[PDB]
């Protein structure tokens, strides 16, 4: 299957949904960052900080301009790299959770061969796996592989891929 | 805004006036307007908010607890030795180097510490003696020069002609700067 | 010479050196117990099996004690005394067993039921081995009271602390049978006498008052609504209090007059008030039941006549529906409002009283805290007040952080207390006179001289002993007419307060702790053995604790944080506070 | 933050760091405490939830000093809607169980005499609470018209003209000029108390 470098719309959605501890589908794009967590002032700024780290440059007044138009405003300058933030986040995902046998590097070639999805399609499925965090203890590698299957289905359904 | 009226008054004047207003009220309410009732200490500060012998001998093993070690060495009295063994940061000029006294006296097996005149700081001498080529000989002599100097003779015995050579460490001990009274002497160092 | 004997439940195992003379007797009863002993599982998660060696020693002690008889000397009495002495020198070295039991809860994966069973087995074996607690226990707290460093006061909880007070009574009956059983059956027989003694008590008690039947068999226990009724509940609360007092006195080795003499003062909450004054009169074990008799008598009559004064009616199903489906309590004649000023609630009750007729009007019963009051009246008129309250109070998840403080809508909680009679109201005034006849007929008197320690009123907080009239009449007046200004009663400067009353976790103790937190007063729940993760109050075990764990003082903010002065060698004065001590500069900064 | 890292590695005399306008996350706090190598950490918690965050930080880090610099909604700069007293009445008990918290009270202080009742702790006696002493004080607006500040003399004259109001009325600064100060939204819509100048 053909590769595709991850967009700024998905990487923005998973970063915003992850920090909230909410599902990738619970958070609508067509809403201001200030409408999301207007409750608290800290959470708003640590959202902006993590988006700033991952994408480098952010526009003036991000929080009051909803997510969708910000997506392409990052997309034009950004170039399909996991960056710094998402690199630490996937590293804590693999190390904090219990795939005690296989690391991130084994996770990549498992998706890459057994499905057939290359580097940019790996990043995209890892962003699905980050927003749907198991949180509770998982048994072994047999649960992890079945979870990676389901995260490849969600990536494929949202983006519009087939396996 | 109710108390902002005086323009171009020095911060010193204002905040001294605040501290002095607090002192006087506290003095009047709990100390009967008597300066003598206020307890005196060498240097005020360096105590963390988390919470009598003239000549003792302490022996560092590989097991000794470094908190209890430095507490025992420094002792209870607030003096130069107290600051010397409990101040975390000395002041090399304006720069904050970690306390090198704690580095040298770090509790490891072999070193033996002797305190002389421990109750009287003016003559207090802490001597640390280590096994130099098997024989346990004196290595460190931390004591006082003229009152406002901390002199740490760091002696080496394995010299050219047997007669060991002393290293003069000096530190100005300014107990008025209670946070980091120990300031290592750079001039002629 | 002693031969080694192994007793084990799977992984957990213990070795007891039985004298070779009595080893054959020991090789028999272990063989019996290893038969009785169930099959150990993983982690000993299943019930009725030990988790620790201490639990298995406990189960052996309990099993041996079950066979051994006190009247008839057997061959098992030597084994019982040898294994008991051995246990006393292998598990609870120094401190009393209660601190050990809690130790098993915090350290091991021991459940509370297993702890209660271990304590029950230990005491059962101790009393069966004819080794009572005669020695004056070396509890740190009461020793420090000996030196006078601690002033100790015992409070007595009222109604509405918990629901299943009888479940606690059952727990007490099972776990401390050997210590309480004697008082329990004495009280049971006393009430059996009182029900027939009263003209029409048998009319009131429709399912009788055979408490010992309900204690022995949980199946025989009537419905919970029968038990919550004041006539039955109030005396049984009394029993639970007195029983707790008995238990602690027997563990301490104190006589009820000795333990009373150790208290600087005592007070109760509503009904509890009578227990303290009954405790204020008791002297010795033989002169104990004469005090209890009077105490258990009054709370019986307080139950009966008050039930006749305002008997609870059948409430419309529509109101119950509304109350339940608007997340409120079951409509009862006492309603607790938290985080709301006295002047606010009195304004609200006045507003409701403006419309209602005098007979159906409500009035403030308990002033527990500044912002924790209880109103009493008709359960329909209380629901009517609830209705007015729900209009004002904001929804429980509404964030008003982004609204300026003044404009904010106040957010309080108003919950129906588990009671069946409106205490400290105008409704229970008529009964007062009938009870005063019930006081005199049964020769129920309280003398100024006979009360040893000062006991405090629930209204003015004055000592009862200075009163001109009958203290019995004053107590009646306090329990059914006068309101409880619980904050006004507790101006006493005591260092430690025992919650003998019912409730345990939700008892009067915790309410008082909250009320006067940070004054250095330490509240101990004497009715429940538990571990507080906050450690901001003690539990039962701290009473029997003899080590440094026994004497724990709560922080008095004024003295602990007292802003001091100091000066340097050069005489520069500093204001010495925590911050200033840290920095070595005055506790004033210019912010960023 | 990475600058301060180097400066602490180089060991310039930087005693502490204070994070204003809210409180960090637990992970960022832990990063700061045992990587920056300060002496202590300042925080300006906005409301009860922020105070609870400070407590959490002080819990996970019980050997590191932590300055809880509480300032009510009445302070200058970016101020919340929180009263100076009530949230302290509620949280003082909880705060004081942690030895490594130093509880600094600020907001609306420009003299020793009005702070003293908070240094003694007798302020709470009015509120029918036990006395609650504090660890220190901060003065924002007091030092504003000092000689050594860089504020322009005419600005100072405008500040000295500012009458100021007692605590009780401060909550009217969201409506009109109350003692020559009014509440205006920030650039990001955070309320700020500014001098009611034509601008």
Image (cartoon, coloured by chain):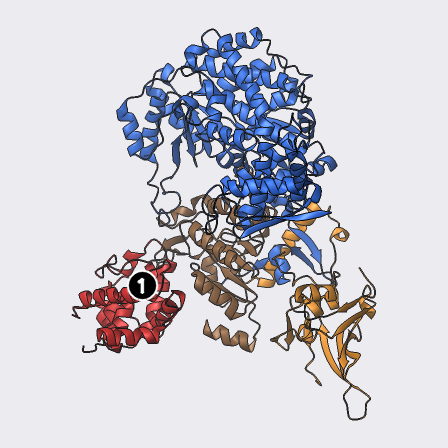
Chain colours: A red, B orange, C blue, D brown
Viewer can see residue C537: no
> Going by the image, does B132 lie left or right of C523?
right
- Viewer-side residue, C295 vs C227: C227
Residue placed under numbered mark 1 in the picture: A143
Residue C539, by quadrant, is top right
- Viewer-side residue, D35 vs C178: C178
- Percent x, y of residue C327: 32, 35
- Percent x, y of residue C552: 63, 44
The image shows residue D170, relative to residue C289, as above or below, that is below
The image shows residue A160, relative to residue C198, as above or below, that is below
How many other residues sit within 10 Å of disc 1, few (<14), some (14-19) or many (≥20)?
A: few
Query: Outermost residue toward the front?
Result: C24
Chain under numbered label 1: A
Residue C338, by quadrant, is top left
Q: Residue at x 70, y 66 (%)?
A: B69
- Percent x, y of residue B61: 71, 70
Q: Residue at x 36, y 25 (%)?
A: C382
> Going by the image, does C156 lie left or right of D26?
right
Residue A26, by quadrant, is bottom left
Please give the count of numbered marks on the rendered protein.
1
Viewer can see residue B9: yes
- Percent x, y of residue D169: 43, 44
The image shows residue A90, relative to residue D59, as above or below, that is below
The image shows residue C564, relative to residue C59, as above or below, that is below
- Viewer-side residue, D121 vs A130: A130
Per the image, label 1 sits on a secondary structure element best described as helix
């Amino acid at each position: 299957i053909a590769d595709e470098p991850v967009k700024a719309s998905l990487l923005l959605h998973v970063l915003v949904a992850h920090k909230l501890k909410k599902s990738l589908d619970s958070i609508p794009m067509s809403k201001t960052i200030k409408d999301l967590v207007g409750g608290k002032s800290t959470v708003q700024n640590e959202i902006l900080g993590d988006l700033g780290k991952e994408f480098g440059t952010t526009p003036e007044k991000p929080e009051e301009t909803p997510l969708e138009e910000l997506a392409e405003t990052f997309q034009d300058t950004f170039s399909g790299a996991l960056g710094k933030q998402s690199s630490s986040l996937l590293s804590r995902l693999i190390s904090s959770k219990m795939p005690g046998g296989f690391t991130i590097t084994v996770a990549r070639k498992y998706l890459q061969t057994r499905w057939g999805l290359p580097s940019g399609r790996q990043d995209g499925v890892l962003l699905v796996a980050l927003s749907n965090e198991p949180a509770a203890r998982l048994g072994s590698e047999a649960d992890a592989k079945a979870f990676l299957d389901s995260m490849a289905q969600k990536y494929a359904s949202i983006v519009g891929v087939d396996l | 805004a109710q108390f902002t009226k005086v323009i171009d008054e020095p911060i010193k004047s204002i905040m001294d006036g605040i501290h002095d207003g607090h002192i006087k009220k506290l003095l009047h309410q709990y100390y009967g307007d008597d300066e003598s009732k206020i307890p005196a200490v060498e240097y005020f500060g360096g105590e963390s908010p988390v919470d009598s012998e003239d000549s003792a001998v302490f022996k560092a093993t590989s097991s000794t607890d470094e908190e209890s070690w430095f507490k025992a060495l420094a002792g209870s009295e607030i003096n130069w030795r107290h600051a010397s063994f409990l101040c975390s940061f000395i002041t090399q000029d304006k720069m904050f180097v970690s306390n090198p006294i704690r580095k040298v006296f770090k509790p490891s097996q072999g070193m033996v510490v002797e305190i002389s005149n421990g109750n009287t700081s003016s003559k207090t001498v802490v001597t640390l003696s280590e096994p130099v080529q098997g024989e346990l000989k004196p290595t460190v002599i931390l004591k006082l020069l003229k009152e406002n100097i901390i002199q740490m003779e760091m002696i080496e015995n394995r010299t050219m002609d047997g007669k060991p050579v002393s290293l003069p460490l000096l530190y100005n001990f300014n107990p008025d700067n209670g946070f980091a009274p120990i300031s290592e002497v750079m001039e002629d160092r | 010479s002693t031969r080694p004997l192994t007793l084990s439940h799977g992984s957990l195992e213990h070795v007891l050196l039985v004298p070779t003379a009595s080893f054959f007797i020991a090789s028999q009863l272990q063989e019996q117990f290893n038969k009785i002993l169930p099959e150990p599982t993983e982690g000993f998660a299943a019930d009725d099996e030990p988790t620790t060696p201490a639990e298995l020693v406990g189960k052996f002690l309990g099993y041996v004690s079950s066979l051994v008889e006190p009247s008839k000397v057997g061959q098992f009495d030597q084994v019982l005394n040898l294994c008991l002495t051995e246990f006393e020198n292998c598990y609870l070295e120094g401190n009393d067993i209660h601190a050990l039991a809690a130790k098993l809860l915090q350290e091991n994966d021991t459940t509370l039921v297993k702890t209660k069973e271990l304590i029950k087995n230990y005491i059962t074996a101790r009393i069966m081995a004819k080794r009572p607690f005669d020695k004056k226990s070396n509890s740190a707290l009461f020793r420090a009271v000996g030196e006078g460093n601690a002033q100790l006061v015992a409070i007595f909880g009222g109604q509405g602390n918990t629901d299943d007070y009888f479940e606690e009574l059952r727990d007490l009956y099972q776990t401390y049978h050997v210590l309480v059983g004697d008082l329990i059956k004495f009280s049971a027989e006393t009430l059996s006498e009182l029900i027939r003694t009263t003209l029409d008590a048998e009319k009131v008690f429709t399912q009788g008052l055979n408490i010992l039947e309900w204690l022995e068999n949980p199946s025989n226990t009537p419905d919970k609504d029968y038990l919550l009724s004041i006539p039955i509940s109030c005396p049984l609360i009394g029993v639970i209090q007195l029983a707790h007092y008995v238990v602690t006195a027997k563990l301490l080795g104190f006589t009820p007059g000795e333990l009373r003499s150790y208290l600087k003062g005592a007070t109760g909450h509503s009904q509890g008030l009578v227990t303290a004054v009954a405790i204020a009169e008791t002297d010795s074990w033989e002169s104990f039941f004469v005090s209890v008799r009077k105490a258990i008598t009054v709370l019986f009559f307080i139950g009966v006549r008050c039930y006749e004064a305002y008997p609870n009616t059948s409430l419309p199903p529509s109101i119950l529906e509304d109350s339940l489906e608007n997340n409120e309590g079951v409509p009862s004649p006492m309603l607790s409002i938290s985080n709301l000023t006295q002047e606010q609630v009195q304004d609200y009750v006045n507003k409701t009283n403006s419309h209602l007729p005098a007979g159906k009007q409500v009035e403030i019963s308990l002033v527990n805290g500044a912002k924790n009051l209880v109103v009493s009246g008709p359960p329909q008129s209380l629901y009517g007040l609830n209705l007015t309250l729900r209009k004002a109070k904001a929804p429980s998840g509404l964030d008003q952080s982004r609204i300026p403080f003044s404009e904010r809508k106040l957010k309080f909680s108003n919950r129906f207390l588990p009671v069946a009679s409106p205490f400290h109201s105008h409704l229970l005034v008529p009964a007062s006179d009938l009870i005063n006849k019930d006081l005199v007929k049964n020769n129920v008197s309280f003398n100024a001289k006979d009360i040893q320690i000062p006991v405090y009123d629930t209204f003015d907080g004055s000592d009862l002993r200075v009163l001109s009239g009958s203290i019995s009449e004053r107590i009646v007046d306090c329990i059914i007419r006068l309101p409880v200004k619980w904050e006004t009663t507790t101006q006493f400067k005591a260092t430690h307060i025992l919650d003998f009353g019912p409730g345990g976790a939700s008892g009067l103790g915790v309410l008082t702790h909250r009320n006067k937190d940070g004054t250095g007063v330490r509240v101990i729940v004497a009715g429940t053995l538990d571990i507080n993760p906050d450690d901001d109050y003690g539990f039962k075990q701290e009473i029997f604790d003899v080590t440094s764990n026994g004497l724990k003082k709560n922080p008095n903010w004024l003295e602990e944080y007292h802003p001091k002065l100091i000066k340097n060698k050069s005489g520069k004065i500093f204001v010495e506070t925590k911050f200033s001590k840290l920095i070595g500069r005055p506790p004033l900064l210019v912010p960023g | 933050i990475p600058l301060i890292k180097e400066l602490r590695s180089k060991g310039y005399p930087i005693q502490f760091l204070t994070i204003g306008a809210g409180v960090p996350s637990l992970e960022v706090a832990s990063e700061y405490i045992e990587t920056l190598g300060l002496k202590y950490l300042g925080l300006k918690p906005g409301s009860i939830d922020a105070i609870s965050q400070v407590i959490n930080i002080a819990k996970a880090h019980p050997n590191f000093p932590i300055a809880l610099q509480w300032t009510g909604g009445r302070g200058g700069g970016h101020h919340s809607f929180e009263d100076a007293h009530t949230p302290m009445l509620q949280m003082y008990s909880k705060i004081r169980r942690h030895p490594n918290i130093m509880l600094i009270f600020g907001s609306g202080f420009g003299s020793a005499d009005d702070t003293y009742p908070y240094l003694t702790g007798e302020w709470s006696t009015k509120f029918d609470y036990p006395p609650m002493p504090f660890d220190g004080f901060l003065f924002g607006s007091r030092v504003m018209i000092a000689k050594e500040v860089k504020t322009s003399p005419d600005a100072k004259k405008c500040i000295a003209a500012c009458t100021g109001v007692p605590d009780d009325k401060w909550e009217q600064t969201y409506k009109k000029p109350t003692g020559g100060i009014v509440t205006v939204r920030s650039e990001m819509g955070e309320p700020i108390h500014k001098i009611a100048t034509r601008g």
